[PDB]
Length: 164
Image (cartoon, rainbow, N blue to C red):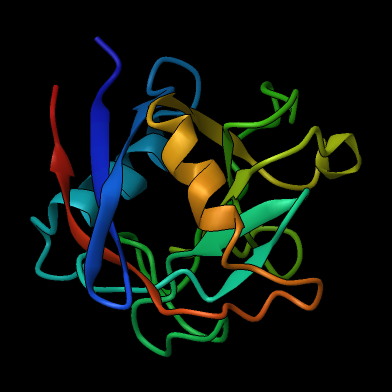
């Protein structure tokens, strides 16, 4: 029942591989739907062609800023921002998909993929999915990050959509 979406990742334009995510629509429907629709582009905007602008090895990969490409932009399908839906799910380890934000009730389009357990984010960032296939591809991406988050090569979502 829960939707599955995929990202095809490229590194300086060269294909790297595919990561797929289960979105927990059963627990966080509003947040899952935002990510799903941004992945298919059905609203006329979304993730295709956007980059991962901040990658910190041993912590997370952050992306979703499709308007400014640097962590200062993005928007949701509901408007500039939407509320924190709930905090039922926790940051339990690598592979968790969670919303980036700039304070309470400021979700847009930015998200991160955790590559470690990040329990200090529990109750602050809405967890809404997990990597299903291709965690090895996330691990490969991680190697292009750095301590300050700057990437050594351009990491992009070359294609994305819904599988199921």
